Length: 211
Image (cartoon, rainbow, N blue to C red):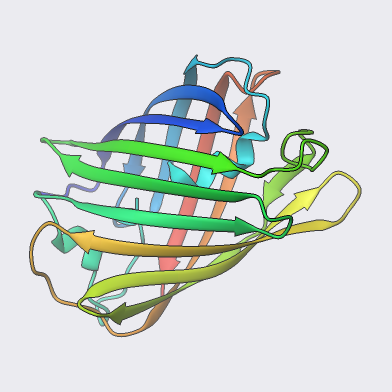
């Protein structure tokens, strides 16, 4: 079912501070190593007037190295798939809502992603393209009301050395009943390996591990 090497195709539709945009993506990931890499192309809205980083955590926990003594809520959900709903509240009251539906058809995961963001101060780091990278983080995962949830504090590094903080709250729902895991934590790291001037092309690498 879930082979060691799984291709990925994804499409993100959305809008940030009104600016509407579309990003297609294709890549490959190692589910059992907890790794993946995506090539991401802006099809609509180029050049993006906002920092690309606010989008990177939105492009799948199937690619999460899980120990044998934790239930993998995300690999069990297949081949049917699962979905997640994420709210990301930034410290300057900029707010984003994203939602991903994740299916699979063979050796290929498929993501349908919606992304919306608003109230980003036009002179804030987002609309002024002043972010650098997401700081390595850990996601506190806990079962609640029969669905999985993941909370985390995220920190973008800024031009100037400061840290632009954000609160991520995610609700994961599988398309069938699976073994609910206890409360655990997923350490993950997201990197932009390469990108062209206006981030119209982005190679994005993610590494995650549960514990």
